[PDB]
């Protein structure tokens, strides 16, 4: 997005990112940069140890034996990818990680969760992973030579609006990685076809004045509430409370049977 | 995931000391229990389709409302997803039985299953009832005495029963 | 001619342990790739190494984009 | 973790499959190996302190300069010697973990991954640790399957460092 | 085909790794199971004709309509019976291959992959082949490890069919 | 991929016949050599770095033109690439020794290597000579009677020798 | 790709000795010419749209069969593709002028261009005629004496003319 | 290579853009630096032999064990000394190439990429080459822009080694 | 946005490397250009109204139809004239921003990206703005590096419009 929304949302680096294309007759440093970009984006910005590097796959990429898409596929099918994104993760979290790493976006629909779940159950991890890389979406956006990059913050064709909002649930910042087993943030949002408010970068903070307590910190409590007292006006509720009233607010939410969806510093 | 051995290893590495003698003898006792563990895994695996189908049939018999039109197991795709969920739960129970540790069952299957069900409207209590049906069906299969060397499999049966209960508790 | 180590999936299917080289020509701008973010760099003979299990996909991909599969050779 | 049981379940789960006879044979091999591996771990544990001190002295003998030249990366002072003894103790302790787990998985996760950056940043020669591992391999006093499994882990570390 | 040895190599090659103690343990498990598998295959192929004939007859008795109603998919005529006996022989032969190989790889390679859309295309009910495999389970006469491994492969085919 | 068992299985399935008594006896003899095969794989793996590095140093001792400037082994990236290739060939030879069949070394490493080396300008003769040096080192280490239950390993050494020759002939 | 400095650096590294005094002095002469190199690049870039559009207009006035229906430049998509091609060639010619080496032009622009045009049916001879028209317009823009510090720019003009002839020869 | 002109063209080509004033300023900075870089390459070349022998001798002084310890990776005999002088000459020559090119491109292309695998494989400690480069930076005797540019390349090599 | 300093850092960051002599030369080129760019921006700022009014008047002279044809996109009435002077002022102000920044980055971020579909949806002829930019080019009265940099931004806008 433009700068004025980008600084607020903390997506300036994503907006100014340039797609990396491995051209013909590329030099050694270009292949090095392409390999580094693939490792950064497919492995979700983890500190990749040299012992976890795919030496044979990057050799084939260097020697023009395979394309960038094939190297992306080799990294995605690698046991390193399995260990940090599949073997200790629930299936819904795993496929949103696949969507972020391979297509650069958040899941659009619960049917996309229904897909890749049956596909896993019928054809294994390899077929399920190949679905993303062989998809029509991967071909027009990245092709055989462009490193995949995150696209959820920009308006795409055949895109649902929720994708942009849901993007901030899967991209938590430039200095973030997908490293810690964790559950998806999009489960209820995808299942019930909703959208969650975006609280990223500086968007989450709210005015404090003299209303915040001793340590001048407000917390936003997003809860799901029903009538258990006073009339409930909305199913969704947001509560801004100081630190000193955080335990009391939590306990009275608990005794009303209200489900807490999120707590963030505001 | 962890197995029965790596679980002790990870705790020891975090504490930064070698496994004590007692931990080594405990793992050795697990080793002496290994053939019966493999037999139980093989027996549940060999009857897995029968286990899932019979448990599902019994579950839909006592809960006609699951398969009633508008019910959560109505329509072919939802019913197929339901049978898939039964099969998935049974498979990770066998994985947990094989490893001697519940991490694969917890991390891959049970983590997030409850709120997935709640979000989607899949009745977790009915899933728990189906898992309980697979429980006794598989425990009779594991404890079947004919065509196997005799011995006490009560400890293995208790462990497999615990995995099934953990699954039943997680989905509800 | 290398590649089979990484192109063939880690699944040990004997059928899947077969890769083939596709020669494609005439990768034009068509109505199928109007919204392609990347641009076509070569329209002459390009060589794509395809494992057996994805030959169904790739030829479809080639056929939507106007590419002509002129030859297919065992690797 | 690179251990036979986790490996078998990882392969099956990646394939979305039940545990077949292939996985059962993996467990059978793990069972056939585990007692020898466990008593190798206990033999290494009971002799661990003497092995580490002996391994440390062997490194000091083969590379005498490490005990003389000043520098943070050397063992000239008592602080450096404690760091050296702690490192060799780490090598031996995760090797026992490998014997308990039946694979190189403890070595990979705890020690092997990123060790090259460590030895480069703090200018530690990997050849020192290779000498420590060679002493341990030559002085653990094991036999048979215990020797074979323990030597495989020690040589795995040796090959990783070189 | 999926076998203990090849799966160990394939996952080691996926990681660019040499064969560690984990793969050696898998091979040891394969070695422990291999003699029983070879002895089971020999025993199964000795009376393979009797087993196939009895299994075909068991299917005919369990499903009498197969020998009565006309149809390409039924065994009313001799052509249907020859096709049926050939199918049972296919199932039994690939099971012996599985016993030899040490995994369900031959079944997946030659029989399991694509069997359901074959059965749908040619209107063959999987229940027929389940009865045949159940007869093979009940009348092979194997004991010990050979019985357990052969039954695991036979139950794998049954579970894939049903 | 094929191992020693699936190779005869594939041949038998193509002919659509059961394995004869002679084939099963040959497989039984293979099982009787299984301990020696595992020992050979373990010994080469435990000396992999030494074999590759000593062979590379010997390969650059003679034939000095590889490491002179303008040579193929000159510059750090190309030296690292050469060292990497020696280790890769050795790794796939161990895979072939482990499986008892040469399919893994040929299909994943050898087939297409000669044309690849010709296109890059890599001297196939020199890399074949390095493979020959790796051959001699590995065979000495496998045929080391110290610290092992002494026995006749002539058959497994001949198989390893055949795999190394296969690597050298395919790369030259 | 190389620049004027890295080209002799790569040649020296392959030969394996330091740059000679003559090579260093020649690069110093290149540095002296560098201001005129930057000015030429800037002048071509500032008239990039004019050069491309005027050359295309000239290439369609004569040779009218390109823009006639059925011609290769007929329809908006092909015409836009043709204009994009002229701009791309001009852009890579400026790249080669900026670097002082034609490697960017060869590797990233002209590589496979003849085969691309033969496979599309693009009349590469006509593309070469358009490139020559771009060449003459670009050369008289570079050699424009007013509004700039007078000097002999014959060498940089010859280098630019060589790049243009190289593009025209590759496409023809 | 990582030189200013090629990087400017690379970043312009990745966006599909003509060269603008930003790229022109890059070339102007390249022109400002090139003459100082070129006499520096000339001065380093003119004094190359003494610098290489002095750097090698400095390494032998700081690490005496390399002078008298048997081993292929050590310079005990002439063979190992020649190799050491050849390596230091490689370092110095590529540094002059970097001065000519105006960037760390030659160091990356010829020396930096893959150096740590070489050092690990042949058991050569990067501390040796760090001291050699330190000698070069202390005794090349340049001043001003030439010294700063030359020191940047030598420090770049030092940082990659450490 | 696109400046020598920011693009140097972004290129270095995408390759995960520290800033080397290449980026230092880029900054040096920026410094050599920056003083002339700043005083060019000052000269354009001081003469902004005369330049904007003269350029707008020049567009009206060369395109008289814009002054008597009725329509939202034309300057026949005062509202159209106000939009036109504001648009040319937008162009001139952003050009001064480019001179300050040392690159076309302000033009790309503020004006160039999306300019074509704005001209299309509001039926604004880019030839009008090209003539305005040509007047600014011919009447800014700058010299030397100031003229060169300022003209590069102006005809960058011209090239983007045509
Ligand atoms: C040629 C290869 C050399 C050789 C080998 C040899 N080995 C054995 C027997 C055994 N070797 C093992 C191996 C291992 N046990 C472990 O725990 C590990 C680590 C996972 C390994 C590699 C085993 C289990 C046996 C069987 C029991 C025993 O110790 O004897 C033999 C004996 C015959 C046989 O094949 O069983 C032989 C011949 N002997 C030589 O002389 C060659 C140098
Ligand atoms: C115009 C009337 C108002 C206005 C608009 C404005 N919108 C954006 C940015 C975005 N718009 C969308 C919306 C969609 N994208 C889709 O794919 C779909 C269809 C399913 C919709 C509805 C999104 C997601 C964005 C952000 C991503 C993108 O810009 O591509 C902007 C730009 C904001 C910025 O800072 O760049 C603007 C200006 N602004 C106004 O002031 C008008 C009232
Ligand atoms: C060292 C002083 C302390 C410490 C550090 C530590 N950090 C991590 C993990 C990560 N570090 C980052 C940070 C970045 N990655 C980037 O790309 C950027 C640039 C924008 C930054 C700032 C990230 C994202 C991670 C996540 C994991 C990853 O591998 O990338 C760890 C690892 C934790 C773990 O392995 O579980 C550690 C140890 N730890 C200390 O104790 C020091 C105080
Ligand atoms: C059957 C006994 C009950 C039932 C089941 C049911 N489940 C779903 C949907 C999902 N189930 C899961 C769970 C998993 N998928 C996995 O891949 C894993 C293993 C790693 C697990 C644990 C998920 C994620 C979903 C959602 C995605 C999907 O649709 O597959 C449904 C469908 C719900 C819907 O269509 O909205 C059903 C029907 N339903 C009953 O009524 C039974 C009690
Ligand atoms: C002993 C053989 C030689 C030696 C040792 C020495 N090591 C360090 C410092 C470190 N050693 C490690 C290694 C590890 N940490 C781990 O967690 C593990 C995996 C379980 C390993 C292998 C690390 C990380 C450091 C640096 C941090 C720390 O100080 O602990 C030093 C000190 C270096 C310094 O600058 O402080 C020394 C001296 N020195 C000798 O001379 C021996 C021959
Ligand atoms: C016997 C249990 C019942 C039966 C048999 C029957 N089968 C067919 C035809 C086919 N059988 C197969 C099956 C396989 N072919 C293979 O290659 C393998 C795996 C290695 C298997 C298991 C196939 C593919 C066919 C169709 C093609 C062919 O005819 O070969 C028939 C004929 C059906 C038809 O439409 O022609 C029959 C009769 N039918 C009964 O009634 C028995 C109870
Ligand atoms: C426990 C739930 C039940 C039980 C089990 C039991 N099994 C054994 C012993 C063995 N079982 C096996 C298993 C297999 N052999 C194979 O080839 C395969 C298929 C690939 C399998 C699954 C083996 C190898 C043994 C050891 C040899 C033997 O058969 O004796 C025991 C005996 C104790 C032991 O641990 O060895 C027991 C108790 N017995 C019951 O009564 C339960 C119903
Ligand atoms: C060393 C003994 C000889 C030597 C080697 C050398 N090889 C290359 C380049 C490549 N080698 C391969 C081969 C493989 N890569 C793999 O992943 C596998 C398994 C599938 C193999 C067999 C490939 C693909 C390349 C190209 C990619 C790359 O360069 O890394 C080089 C470098 C050539 C160059 O940089 O242009 C070298 C130097 N060179 C000798 O002189 C020895 C005889
Ligand atoms: C114009 C002077 C002549 C002309 C041109 C024309 N070209 C194409 C199509 C392509 N041109 C290229 C070339 C390149 N693309 C790049 O990215 C680069 C840098 C490597 C180059 C040099 C390519 C690849 C194509 C095809 C794909 C694409 O259009 O992007 C066409 C269109 C042909 C068609 O049928 O679509 C045309 C018309 N035609 C004339 O008549 C002029 C003489
Ligand atoms: C050669 C084809 C024509 C020519 C050129 C010429 N230019 C100079 C000198 C300079 N040109 C510049 C250029 C720029 N300064 C800027 O700020 C910008 C934008 C980034 C540019 C393009 C500079 C800095 C100089 C030096 C100072 C000066 O203004 O003179 C010369 C003089 C010799 C030299 O090499 O410097 C020449 C010859 N002159 C012609 O007659 C040709 C038509
Ligand atoms: C000198 C500071 C110390 C030393 C040196 C030494 N080096 C080697 C061997 C090699 N050196 C290299 C390095 C490079 N090769 C290149 O092409 C470049 C980049 C342009 C570099 C930096 C390599 C690759 C080798 C190994 C291959 C070869 O033999 O050339 C040795 C010999 C090692 C051996 O095993 O024979 C030595 C002795 N030794 C000391 O003791 C000094 C302190
Ligand atoms: C003047 C040269 C000619 C002219 C001008 C004219 N412009 C508009 C309308 C708009 N102008 C813009 C342009 C910009 N907005 C920006 O934010 C920037 C970048 C910083 C630019 C360059 C836009 C977006 C509009 C439309 C919205 C608006 O009215 O502000 C009009 C009016 C068109 C209408 O329908 O309202 C006019 C008249 N008209 C002439 O005749 C001159 C030759």
Image (cartoon, coloured by chain):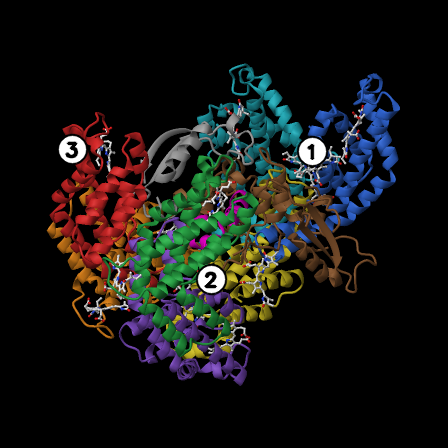
Chain colours: A brown, B green, D purple, E red, F orange, G cyan, H yellow, I blue
Label 1 and label 2: CA atoms lie apart by 47 Å
Percent across and percent down for residue H129 are 50, 69
Label 2 and label 3: CA atoms lie apart by 69 Å
Percent across and percent down for residue I114 are 69, 33
Dot 1 crowding, Cα within 10 Å, few <14, some 14–19, many 20+: few
Residue occupied by mark 1:
I114
**Is the CB of the residue bearing disc 2 within 8 angstroms of ligand 11?**
yes
Q: Which residues are magenta?
A: A75-104
Using the image, tell me which numbered label, if any, was put on residue D59: none
**Is D36 in front, or is G97?**
D36
Callout in the foreground (1, 2) = 1
Q: Is residue I1 above or below residue D50?
A: above
Magenta stretch: dominant secondary structure: helix
Q: Is residue D69 left or right of residue E157?
A: right
Q: Is the residue under label 3 in contact with that under label 1 (CB below 8 Å)?
A: no
Label 1 and label 3: CA atoms lie apart by 74 Å
For image coordinates 72% across by 58% down, the residue present is: A249
Chain of the residue on which disc 2 is drawn: H
**Is A30 in front, or is H70?**
A30
In the rendered image, residues at marks 1 and 2 fall on the same chain: no
Residue occupied by mark 3:
E82
> What SS does tag 1 mark?
loop
Q: Is the residue under label 2 in contact with that under label 1 (CB below 8 Å)?
A: no
Residue occupied by mark 2:
H115
Chain of the residue on which disc 3 is drawn: E
For image coordinates 43% across by 40% down, the residue present is: B80
Q: Is residue D126 above or below residue I157?
A: below
Q: Is residue A260 left or right of residue A132?
A: right
Callout in the foreground (1, 3) = 3
> What SS does tag 2 mark?
helix
Taking the magenta stretch, the answer to whether it contains residue A90 is yes
Percent across and percent down for residue E150 are 22, 52
């Amino acid at each position: 997005t433009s700068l004025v929304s980008a600084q607020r949302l903390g997506i300036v680096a994503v907006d100014e990112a340039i797609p990396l294309e491995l051209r013909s007759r590329s030099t050694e440093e270009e292949v090095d940069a392409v390999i580094l970009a693939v490792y950064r984006q497919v492995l979700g910005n983890d500190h990749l140890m040299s012992q976890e590097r795919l030496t044979s796959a990057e050799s084939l990429l260097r020697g023009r034996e395979i394309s960038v898409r094939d190297f992306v596929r080799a990294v995605a099918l690698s046991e390193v990818y399995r260990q940090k994104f599949f073997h200790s993760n629930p299936q819904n979290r795993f496929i949103e990680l696949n969507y972020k790493h391979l297509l650069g976006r958040a899941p659009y629909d619960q049917s996309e969760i229904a897909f890749h779940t049956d596909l896993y159950h019928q054809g294994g991890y390899e077929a399920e992973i190949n679905s993303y890389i062989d998809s029509v979406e991967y071909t027009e956006n990245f092709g055989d030579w462009v490193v995949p990059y995150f696209r959820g913050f920009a308006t795409q064709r055949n895109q649902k609006t929720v994708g942009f909002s849901r993007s901030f649930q899967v991209y938590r910042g430039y200095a973030t990685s997908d490293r810690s087993g964790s559950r998806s943030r999009l489960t209820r949002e995808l299942a019930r076809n909703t959208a969650s408010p975006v609280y990223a970068g500086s968007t989450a903070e709210s005015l404090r004045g003299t209303s915040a307590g001793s340590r001048n910190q407000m917390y936003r409590l997003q809860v799901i509430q029903g009538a258990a007292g006073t009339r409930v006006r909305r199913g969704k509720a947001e509560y801004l409370v100081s630190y000193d009233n955080l335990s009391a607010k939590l306990q009275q939410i608990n005794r009303q049977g209200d489900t807490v969806t999120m707590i963030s510093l505001a | 995931m962890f197995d029965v051995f790596t679980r002790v290893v990870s705790q020891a590495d975090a504490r930064g000391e070698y496994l004590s003698g007692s931990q080594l003898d405990a793992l050795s006792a697990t080793v002496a229990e290994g053939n019966k563990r493999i037999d139980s895994v093989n027996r549940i695996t060999g009857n897995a389709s029968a286990i899932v189908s019979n448990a599902a049939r019994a579950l839909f018999a006592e809960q006609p409302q699951l398969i009633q039109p508008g019910g959560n197991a109505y329509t072919s795709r939802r019913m197929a997803a339901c049978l898939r969920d039964m099969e998935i739960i049974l498979r990770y129970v066998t994985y947990a039985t094989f490893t001697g540790d519940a991490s694969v069952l917890e991390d891959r299957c049970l983590n997030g299953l409850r709120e997935t069900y709640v979000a989607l409207g899949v009745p977790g209590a009915s899933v728990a009832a189906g898992v309980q049906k697979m429980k006794e069906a598989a425990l009779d299969i594991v404890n079947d005495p004919n065509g196997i060397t005799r011995g006490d499999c009560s400890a293995i049966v208790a462990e497999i029963a615990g995995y099934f209960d953990r699954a039943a508790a997680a989905v509800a | 001619m290398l590649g089979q180590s990484s192109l063939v999936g880690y699944s040990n299917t004997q059928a899947a342990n077969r890769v083939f080289v596709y020669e494609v020509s005439g990768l034009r701008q068509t109505d199928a790739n109007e919204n392609s973010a990347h641009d076509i760099r070569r329209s002459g003979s390009v060589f794509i190494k395809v494992p057996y299990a994805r030959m169904n996909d790739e030829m479809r991909r080639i056929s939507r984009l106007g590419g002509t599969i002129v030859n297919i050779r065992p690797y | 973790m690179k251990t036979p049981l986790t490996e078998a379940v990882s392969t099956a789960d990646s394939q979305g499959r039940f545990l077949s006879s292939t996985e059962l044979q993996i467990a059978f091999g793990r069972l056939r190996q585990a007692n020898a591996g466990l008593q190798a771990a206990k033999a290494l544990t009971d002799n661990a302190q003497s092995l580490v001190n002996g391994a440390a002295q062997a490194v000091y003998n083969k590379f005498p300069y490490t005990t003389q030249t000043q520098g943070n990366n050397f063992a000239a002072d008592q602080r450096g010697k404690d760091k050296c003894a702690r490192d060799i103790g780490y090598y031996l302790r995760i090797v026992t973990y490998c014997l308990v787990a039946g694979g190189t998985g403890p070595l990979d996760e705890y020690l092997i991954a990123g060790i090259d950056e460590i030895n480069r940043t703090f200018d530690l020669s990997p050849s020192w640790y290779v000498e420590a591992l060679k002493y341990i391999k030559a002085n653990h006093g094991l036999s048979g399957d215990a020797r074979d499994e323990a030597n495989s882990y020690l040589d795995y570390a040796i090959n990783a460092l070189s």
